[PDB]
Image 1: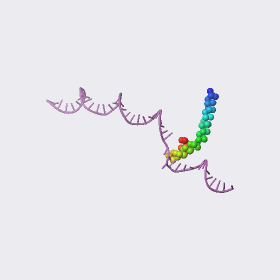
Image 2: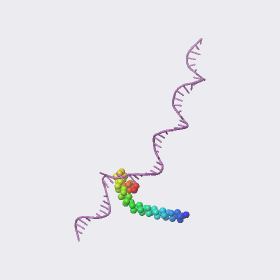
Image 3: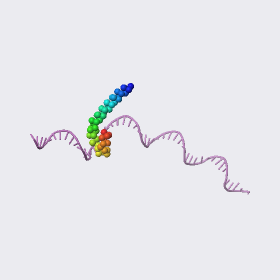
Image 4: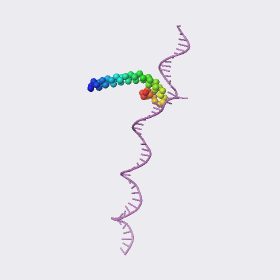
Length: 51
DNA sequence: CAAAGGCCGAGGAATGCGCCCTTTTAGCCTTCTTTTGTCAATGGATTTGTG
Protein backbone atom coordinates (compact mmCIF):
# COMPACT_ATOMS: atom_id res chain seq x y z
CA UNK A 1 0.00 0.00 0.00
CA UNK A 2 3.05 2.22 0.52
CA UNK A 3 4.02 1.72 -3.12
CA UNK A 4 0.38 2.13 -4.20
CA UNK A 5 0.02 5.56 -2.60
CA UNK A 6 3.54 6.25 -3.85
CA UNK A 7 2.57 5.66 -7.48
CA UNK A 8 -0.48 7.81 -6.81
CA UNK A 9 1.85 10.56 -5.58
CA UNK A 10 4.04 10.15 -8.66
CA UNK A 11 1.05 10.67 -10.93
CA UNK A 12 -0.12 13.64 -8.88
CA UNK A 13 3.30 15.31 -8.98
CA UNK A 14 3.59 14.74 -12.73
CA UNK A 15 0.17 16.22 -13.46
CA UNK A 16 0.82 19.11 -11.08
CA UNK A 17 4.08 20.05 -12.76
CA UNK A 18 2.26 19.79 -16.09
CA UNK A 19 -0.49 22.17 -14.95
CA UNK A 20 2.29 24.44 -13.74
CA UNK A 21 3.99 24.45 -17.14
CA UNK A 22 0.73 25.29 -18.89
CA UNK A 23 -0.06 28.15 -16.50
CA UNK A 24 3.48 29.47 -16.91
CA UNK A 25 3.10 29.46 -20.68
CA UNK A 26 -0.26 31.25 -20.71
CA UNK A 27 0.44 33.98 -18.14
CA UNK A 28 0.97 36.23 -21.17
CA UNK A 29 -2.57 35.45 -22.32
CA UNK A 30 -3.88 36.38 -18.90
CA UNK A 31 -2.07 39.72 -18.98
CA UNK A 32 -3.37 40.43 -22.48
CA UNK A 33 -6.94 39.88 -21.31
CA UNK A 34 -6.58 41.84 -18.07
CA UNK A 35 -5.26 44.89 -19.93
CA UNK A 36 -8.83 45.47 -21.13
CA UNK A 37 -10.25 46.16 -17.65
CA UNK A 38 -7.49 48.27 -16.13
CA UNK A 39 -9.50 51.41 -15.47
CA UNK A 40 -12.71 50.07 -13.87
CA UNK A 41 -11.65 50.45 -10.25
CA UNK A 42 -9.25 47.52 -9.76
CA UNK A 43 -5.49 47.84 -10.01
CA UNK A 44 -3.58 46.06 -12.73
CA UNK A 45 -1.92 43.38 -10.61
CA UNK A 46 -5.26 42.51 -9.03
CA UNK A 47 -6.74 41.97 -12.46
CA UNK A 48 -3.81 39.74 -13.37
CA UNK A 49 -4.18 37.73 -10.16
CA UNK A 50 -7.89 37.12 -10.61
CA UNK A 51 -7.08 36.14 -14.17
C1' DC B 1 25.73 49.78 -51.82
C1' DA B 2 21.20 52.71 -48.70
C1' DA B 3 15.85 53.77 -48.10
C1' DA B 4 11.10 53.04 -48.03
C1' DG B 5 8.34 50.51 -46.41
C1' DG B 6 6.11 46.15 -44.51
C1' DC B 7 6.05 43.90 -39.97
C1' DC B 8 5.87 42.99 -35.17
C1' DG B 9 5.95 44.28 -30.56
C1' DA B 10 5.79 47.04 -26.26
C1' DG B 11 2.40 50.78 -23.92
C1' DG B 12 -1.89 53.37 -23.40
C1' DA B 13 -6.72 55.47 -23.22
C1' DA B 14 -11.36 54.25 -23.17
C1' DT B 15 -17.40 54.98 -26.94
C1' DG B 16 -14.78 49.85 -22.79
C1' DC B 17 -18.82 45.81 -19.54
C1' DG B 18 -22.31 38.55 -20.27
C1' DC B 19 -25.62 35.50 -20.48
C1' DC B 20 -28.46 31.85 -19.46
C1' DC B 21 -29.56 28.73 -15.85
C1' DT B 22 -29.48 26.13 -11.32
C1' DT B 23 -29.46 26.61 -6.12
C1' DT B 24 -29.17 28.48 -1.84
C1' DT B 25 -30.28 32.52 1.42
C1' DA B 26 -33.06 36.49 3.42
C1' DG B 27 -36.76 38.16 4.75
C1' DC B 28 -41.72 39.13 4.62
C1' DC B 29 -46.09 37.40 5.47
C1' DT B 30 -49.57 34.74 7.28
C1' DT B 31 -51.40 31.48 11.41
C1' DC B 32 -51.27 29.97 15.66
C1' DT B 33 -49.95 29.35 20.86
C1' DT B 34 -48.86 31.94 25.09
C1' DT B 35 -47.71 35.73 28.24
C1' DT B 36 -49.79 39.86 29.44
C1' DG B 37 -52.74 43.76 30.30
C1' DT B 38 -58.00 44.67 31.29
C1' DC B 39 -63.15 44.77 32.62
C1' DA B 40 -66.60 43.08 35.53
C1' DA B 41 -68.01 40.58 39.70
C1' DT B 42 -68.24 39.31 44.53
C1' DG B 43 -67.43 38.95 48.81
C1' DG B 44 -64.72 40.73 52.78
C1' DA B 45 -62.06 43.83 56.47
C1' DT B 46 -61.73 49.18 58.27
C1' DT B 47 -64.59 53.67 58.38
C1' DT B 48 -68.76 55.96 59.72
C1' DG B 49 -73.74 56.19 61.58
C1' DT B 50 -76.16 55.50 64.92
C1' DG B 51 -77.68 56.59 70.20
